[PDB]
Amino acid sequence: TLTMGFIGFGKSANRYHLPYLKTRNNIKVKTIFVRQINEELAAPYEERGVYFTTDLDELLNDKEIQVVTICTPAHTHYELAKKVILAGKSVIVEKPFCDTVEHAKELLALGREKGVVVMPYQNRRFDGDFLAVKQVVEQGFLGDIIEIESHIDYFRPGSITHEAPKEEGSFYSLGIHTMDRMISLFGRPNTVTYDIRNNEVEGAVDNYFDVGLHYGNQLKIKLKTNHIVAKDYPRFIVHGTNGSFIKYGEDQQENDLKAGIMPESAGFGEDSPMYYGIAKYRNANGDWIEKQIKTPLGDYGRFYDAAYDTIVNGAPKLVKDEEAVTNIEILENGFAAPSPSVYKLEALHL
Amino acid sequence: TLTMGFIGFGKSANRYHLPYLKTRNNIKVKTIFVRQINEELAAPYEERGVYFTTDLLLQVVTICTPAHTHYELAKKVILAGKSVIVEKPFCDTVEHAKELLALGREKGVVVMPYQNRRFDGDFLAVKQVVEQGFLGDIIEIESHIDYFRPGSITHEAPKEEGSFYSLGIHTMDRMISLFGRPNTVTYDIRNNEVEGAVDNYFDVGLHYGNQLKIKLKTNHIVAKDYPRFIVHGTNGSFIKYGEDQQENDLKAGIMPESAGFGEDSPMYYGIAKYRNANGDWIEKQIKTPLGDYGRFYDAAYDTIVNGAPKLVKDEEAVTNIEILENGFAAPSPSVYKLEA
Amino acid sequence: TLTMGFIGFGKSANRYHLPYLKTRNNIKVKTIFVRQINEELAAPYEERGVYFTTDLDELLNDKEIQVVTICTPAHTHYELAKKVILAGSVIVEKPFCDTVEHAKELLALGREKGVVVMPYQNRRFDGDFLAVKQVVEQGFLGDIIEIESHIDYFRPGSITHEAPKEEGSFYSLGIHTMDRMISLFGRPNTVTYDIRNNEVEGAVDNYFDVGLHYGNQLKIKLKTNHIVAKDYPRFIVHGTNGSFIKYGEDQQENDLKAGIMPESAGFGEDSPMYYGIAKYRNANGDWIEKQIKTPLGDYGRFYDAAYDTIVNGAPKLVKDEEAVTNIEILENGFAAPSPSVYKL
Amino acid sequence: TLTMGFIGFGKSANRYHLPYLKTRNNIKVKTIFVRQINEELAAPYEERGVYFTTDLDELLNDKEIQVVTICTPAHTHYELAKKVILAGKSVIVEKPFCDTVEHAKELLALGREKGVVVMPYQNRRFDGDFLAVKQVVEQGFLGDIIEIESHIDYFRPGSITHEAPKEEGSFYSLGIHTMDRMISLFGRPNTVTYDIRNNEVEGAVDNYFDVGLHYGNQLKIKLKTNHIVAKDYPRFIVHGTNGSFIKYGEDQQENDLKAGIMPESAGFGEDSPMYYGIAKYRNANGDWIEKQIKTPLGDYGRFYDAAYDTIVNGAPKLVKDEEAVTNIEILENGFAAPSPSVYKLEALHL
Amino acid sequence: FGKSANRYHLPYLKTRNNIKVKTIFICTPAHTHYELSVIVEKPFCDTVEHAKELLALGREKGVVVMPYQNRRFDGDFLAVKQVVEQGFLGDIIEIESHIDYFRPGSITHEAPKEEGSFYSLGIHTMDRMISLFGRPNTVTYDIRNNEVEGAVDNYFDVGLHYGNQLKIKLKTNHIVAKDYPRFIVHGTNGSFIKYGEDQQENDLKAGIMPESAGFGEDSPMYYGIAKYRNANGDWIEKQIKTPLGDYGRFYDAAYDTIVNGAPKLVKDEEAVTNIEILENGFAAPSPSVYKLEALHL
Amino acid sequence: TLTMGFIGFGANRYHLPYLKTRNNIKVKTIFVRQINEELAAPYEERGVYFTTDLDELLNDQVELAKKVILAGKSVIVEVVMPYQNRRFDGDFLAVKQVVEQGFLGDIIEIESHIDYFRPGSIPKEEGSFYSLGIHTMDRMISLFGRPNTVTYDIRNNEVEGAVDNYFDVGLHYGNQLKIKLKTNHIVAKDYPRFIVHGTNGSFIKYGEDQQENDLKAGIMPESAGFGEDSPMYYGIAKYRNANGDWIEKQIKTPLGDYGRFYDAKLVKDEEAVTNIEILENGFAAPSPSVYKLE
């Protein structure tokens, strides 16, 4: 079985990680590192083989831990991921994988010679809505896709009202997710279009973005996040030469988790029928078709399943290096020049 | 009683002009000019008092001939004591446009572009909403005009005959006559089917500072339509599905005079979802205003006979051709700043 | 101002005729004949200009009564038609005659007298029909390949007795849907039947499936079933450029029963929920799914027609060609056991 | 032509009164009294023949004024209503008509003897949703009405928290509208049931009520107001022996008005067709019928049309004296005993 | 033996192994139920006193005595149970439970209160709300026959008050052409509205037996709808699949107390509170108000 | 476990794909004297044998049929039974389940549809009524039985003298029940897939079984979600119980497994002979016509 450890015990760890791990028989969470142990938030876990320590080395030196998940503040990712790759352990890093496009390459390179797996945490590649469009595009019955719009909107006027560094903005904390899974399906684009700003406060950190990733001359996928959307856009708009696929309703795992409903419970991550995506396409006979597509089951744990299969079964790494590095690049160059801006992408020669 | 003429008589004059004029009792069409007359399609009209010739001289004409001679025929009729109502393209270049404008102002005549789509039902609905302002500070608008005609546009040709110039000029216009002159523009013009053919797709966004941004876009490969209009404010939204039906009813052989003409289907009434001062959410349907292209002339009437200000403003028409042209000044996607 | 009389003062008269003639000034109802007079219903009218008599002759032997409407039961339509015919115009209520002969007779035997003789086809003014009619004329659906017309109910145990074919659904309801469709596509080339009583073998027809083949293309259908829980559309229309489906019947009948009179604002008005849905393609190949606002229906518009035909001699609404055609199909429907076929 | 005046120029006068009067040609608003005239909010009316004064007698002594409308603070209504009746002028009073059922009987009686019309301003008798039920009930196709539920809810958790006098709670502020129009339709009920309280803060003034009006043994009409309703109830529910009428959505005049859309604009008072009430009933033959019922046009101005018709043409008054007294009484006795209570009504003999 | 026995029992046991019937001469008419471990059907008993006694005497011989409240396993009710337990709707401030029909002129006769709508229907909707929120501090009654002035009650509107914040109503009308939601739930963070009753009965009456596929199955069309705001203040509206319903589950818990000894499905304090509320809805001419006192046994 | 063979190839859509999950069965040879590997490639890769020799596949367990039949080998056309796979469609299975428990009472009418909107897409065998019609006709005859009489309306709404691409066929089962089979290549707004009326209620079903659409799409049977109907199309049923109450609810559409045929005799002989009778006697007299049955 796989023996893992954690560095950090905050919100994300307690919501998007551990909860799904209580079901994986093959994964063994041995030790969790924490700056300071919170008896109330640690007890529940200590009642299990889990050990909390305040000494980082006491985990980095443990020849038992095989991989460790870093989920602490962004200002500490590069350093930590490097220290863990230094020991003979694999890493799993929460957004952002790294600060600069250079550091990311380095880390990935270091992991190779050390013969360990370095991989960013892209759980939202297991969202039902995404999984649904993934499936469709995979079956290719919609023909050749020419446009795909992806939204992550809210109605929170007044939410973001202060200035801050680019890493604490929408594009960085939310775009990474949408952009990531689109890149994992269609590849690295040739050119990118940027619209990033704060529609409510001049210089405040970005709380709005509209990013276009151009693939050739036909295909383009848009990444849109707005915090002032009263009536939601479709979660995913997909147009192909043969038809379309519209999917309303986002994955509910995040809401269930926020409402004490955990993964083991029945129907968890199950989408509402009213929100099943609608497909409208004409077949070879020119016959128009309009049907619903049962939304795939959204399970964030599936990320931990691929990491288990990638480490102990040499299976192919879920998040390829090319995507991981491409993500940082697009994300980093959005702030290279005032918005709106354009930026071409040269091939990746790793 | 206004007296006008028609420099042309193509598919256009026989669908967006004449059919609406047989109701404007205050307007009289004395003569239609055409190189090669077609009695078959000109018989009904002739039998009502309109004469046709192939030459010239008598207070306003409408250019609807091929979109090339417009400028040439434009400054030609201004040179005569006659007001001008030009069809799109109003002018090839921005200088030529500002030219005709200057000439008109001194020649003592009225000159403006034919923006019939400013009276489209769908547009009139989001115009009404924006005026009343219960949606607060508008932050985004998206105007669509799509089709699903895969295989349609598949040949090279000048920018003057692509979607961005054909369809595009309409959506861009009504959006500008509502917000003004953008401080910068985003261009993504191309052909999603034939790498070099004239553009059959575009995604143009007009930026207005940090707050406002309106997007205009056409695509010919949309099987399930987007809403004709998406409007987001700081207090709520307004989504409108379904396009104005005037055009379609015209092709069906249905004319302006008939009943129900230009009436929207209830099922397509746009939905506004916003919250009042108290914070209560309200979600209601907005009755679509009646679409009527004939209003272009009615309004033009009050301008040439009652002096009332024209529908299309100068700042408008010019700013309209500028955005339209600079979308080629570079390969797309490109950005372009607009100065006063 | 045309002057008329009525032979009968039952439900029909007091529902599809009188209330509508209340706003029609040019028409005057001088006298009404009935076997037995019920003052309760007479008074409101008597308070106006109207004489209620119990002697048939009182009416027929009048000089200013130019036209009379026969609303008395069907088992007396034929003979009575003659009475008014053998004197000064006749408007007979469904069903005109029982045989194409009597129908042919009364029809012509009326021109040798100098009076108009047309049947009562009020449902040729139903909004749902005015809708398909408005669609067909504009013809954007192209060449109509088929049309389905329903008039169903859900009344098990409804009709159990046997009776002449004049008192059957086909005659009572069929004449309505068949009429307006014939008034639209003319006389057919051949007709298919299927008449019976899906509940009581002997009982009079309470169900009927009739097809009117118009050549090789068009084929209008007419159906009525007293055992339908979930309604069929009120009107199905398929063409070469698209379709038009209309749910919900005209509401004048429901409003009349609930006491809402013709003159009331909103009378007969159809609800959006039931507006017909049209889906077709244009010359560009684009698809279009839009709603067709149901046109307002007015059963009075019939008396407005019979008015012109009598005063300004305007073209008679129900062509003698349609009247005779309708009865022909209606009659031959029992020539041989069902199902059957019959050409014209 | 009817010549009237106003005592007060606050929010309600500039919202539910004047905007509608600027279209009834037969009515002339001559003078408006107010302690302080806001030249801005007064200019437009001044552009017309309306005089603004801070001297009450300047209005009461004006012999040209036939009727006045008191829309000034509630605590002053009984006083002013009287001071105006003592002068030969009819009175239109905003809510509350009076503070006590005893005072109400007084003003009405002083009115009959003084020869002038005296009636409370019940604009809500012209909300579109209410007109629809009034239309259906009169047409009588639903048969005998057995039950009818009337709602006025919101989702404002926390909105009401401080304790204050009853005249300030929901039952007195909203209940006077829903109870008034139901009573104007069915009459004085035999017994009333009361559920009045604050479902958030015990002692706080009432922000909730569920009042039952019983008519004999067959009919009961419920008046309901709750400030914690996320998913709306139907605005009206009507059940009768032959079927029912359910109506969703509330009349939009107030929202429009609040938004700045005036009574003369387009579509004002017209209901969204998606909200037309739905009627399901069986006819005498047993057939079932389900249809929408186009919502009548909502127009608070009709109150003035009715006032006019009565004061100038002697037409029967809108708000009957018995309806006025019954409103105050049912409202007053809701506090006569602790909630949940029951109260028995006796016939009136004004 | 008869209606209930052949309807809401046997068919469910014909799939149970640990259980095995045999004999049958506990579904005696509502008139005669007191006299007769016991599994009494609804209503359990007539008066409050008779109820306690009928239960205490059972705690003497050392056997288990519990009323048959099978609708605690209706899909619709389970849905609101699951939602309330999860608590995303915050503090419940009101819930309305409906059981209506459109059967005009159905009831026009007179009879004992025990065989009235409130007793033979109120008990089903009252019990489950009681087994989730407990005994109420005060009850409100509106019980009558809206068709015949003196016939047995065929209508009722009863409100159970839980303090100052919570109230839940139980309503039954036989004259409702257009249905209310089956359950309406309002709370400080949102609502849950549920249209469409448990289908077991419809299938039972349609000959479809419990031991077959699709039984009790609810359709999406009727999946309750939840609308509420999360902590971020975001509005969420979603359908909530309806928990499969099975009346058989009643025995699984009864049997679970006889041979195993698990906690009795229907707690004593509940069953006693039930018959108490029923009986007092009559201790006075409607409408009336009955304050509940604390229980002690 | 039995062995089988295919007297043809191509079948590569409504046959093989399904069989490759039925362990106790295995193909052998595909009688084809022109088996172009360009297509039979996939299958070739599988443990199957592509031959072209007559007796090779005519000697070894299960017109052109006469031959296959003459030998001791059982055959299935399209133990001897014809291939009626569409008896396992979601729609039909639904309209079938409802009748089995028949809470609708006594069925009195039902319309089976299969339409398209292919304007210009155009002997009796080549006939739409023959090829398509037998599909909608077989299952109905499989549920009720043999009708007394039958009504025909065969023709081509396209070009006067061309193969039949439309038809309205009624099957009068006495004086009460009447099932109608309809097909039209000109329908922009589809009818329901099935209409079923009865003494106590109705059941209307929209949307056809998706197996075919999945197949021509690239979705093989063994995959998940294959053949699942969208809730959007679950059938609706309005019916009154014995108490008089009206009940309206959806009916989950049963999973459509064409492969269920092989698992099976299913197709009765009479149903089979009767099936072909009506097909034939429908072209006798010109249309519109009628034809009684013995």
Image (cartoon, coloured by chain):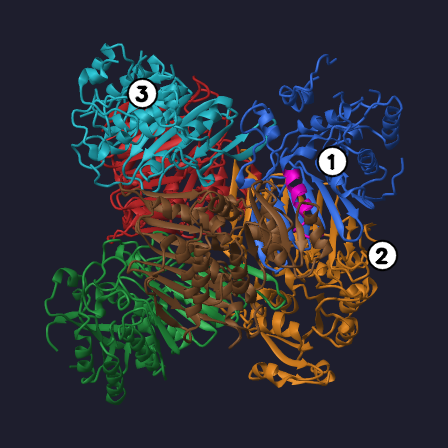
Chain colours: A brown, B green, C red, D orange, E blue, F cyan
**Residue B213 disc label:** none
Label 1 sits on what residue type? Gly
**Is C251 located above or below residue B219 in the figure?**
above
Q: Specify start and end residues of the magenta stretch as a single range.
A: E76-91
- Residue position for label 2: D336
The N terminus of chain F: image quadrant: top left
- Residue position for label 3: F150
Direction from residue D153 to residue F17 in the image, left or right? left
**Residue D77 on image: x %, y %:** 76, 72
Q: Are tags 2 and 1 found on a single chain?
A: no
Label 3 sits on what residue type? Val
Chain letter of disc 2? D
**Is E57 located above or below residue F189 in the figure?**
above
Q: Nearer the viewer, residue C39 or F100?
A: F100
**Is D113 located above or below residue F20 in the figure?**
below
- Does residue D155 belong to the magenta stretch? no
Q: Are tags 3 and 2 found on a single chain?
A: no
Residue lying at 67% horizontally and 53% vertically, measured from the top left: A52
- Does residue E86 belong to the magenta stretch? yes
Q: How many badges with numbers are in the image?
A: 3
**Residue A194 on image: x %, y %:** 40, 68
Q: What secondary structure is found at the residue carrying circle 3?
A: strand
Residue lying at 23% horizontally and 88% vertically, measured from the top left: B107
